[PDB]
Length: 212
Length: 213
Ligand code: NA
Ligand code: NA
Image (cartoon, rainbow over all chains, first blue to last red; front, side):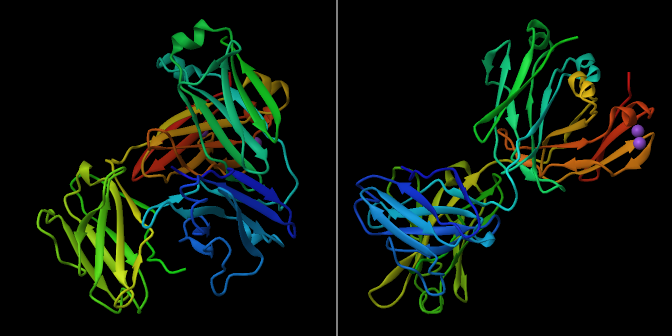
């Protein structure tokens, strides 16, 4: 069973952050064999900590590790922009078996937090004339680069047919993403409205669209 | 702190060949002819595939082969089959009585054919126009691999100002999706006769056109 980590955390340059990683008494709690890895996208992982608290040669002392019960912790002090990466824990579940955490993305805040602009598009006429009814929810100009998207039909949940893209930085150094909802024309015309609800930093924006 | 470095995961198509790498040091992989390879399916006991770099036990298919060069060892799986989907681990002697193991590689077996993108061009929405904005969205979906080139036109003429295109991301069907949006004022939108989104993917081109109404 995988080890449990928070999906993300953020801090300002110079701050201290802490990442926790929770397992069971058969792995994290059974041995002092917890290791921490830093991975930038596309690069091989770098070992930061091994055996709970030991640093390999050449690893900065800004990184420290500890453990209490079935939870191991990685602390990063003096947060620097180069520390923006994915961090995952690893632990022995036995002599040869290892279990891995799900990874925590560390965001180093390089600009003010920005709530997203949300623009919802009904199906185009070309689309409906072709018996398609895809809706697109454009989400732009937000920071940091994480949002939660939920669709609705007449104020009821809709989970099937939804695809949301991973946020990516645009030219204004803010993040953009889109979510689209594949619908048949019958679904589109049988409801009074469809809604795209976008949540960012606990704040929620909902846009609504209706057949015409 | 020692471990043999393996890529976390690779993937290949049925029938093709893949090669896993296993990087050690001059004191283990590079020092001896004693690299082994194991295959493990979830919840099952590991199976020795290769020992002493390239020797194959009886009962192991000859589709598995091992080699090494310098401080890096390699396992090759020819004629990839669905049953080959598993975790693969390398190990090497670090000395007479010591051994180092690898971090493991998940081998996923999945057909991933090329696919040209579906392109849907959206004109400005009503609420957007009443807020004095007229963004156009070009939805680009269901393509593989994850690289496209988007070009916008107005009146058949190239337009690069005010366009943003998201980095393509893999969707639930293992194909990629992205969107390109063009930021206009309502006045710009109405002052043109035509707007077009042209998507290029592997020597294939799709152009969609929309006009104000
Ligand atoms: Na113009
Ligand atoms: Na045009």
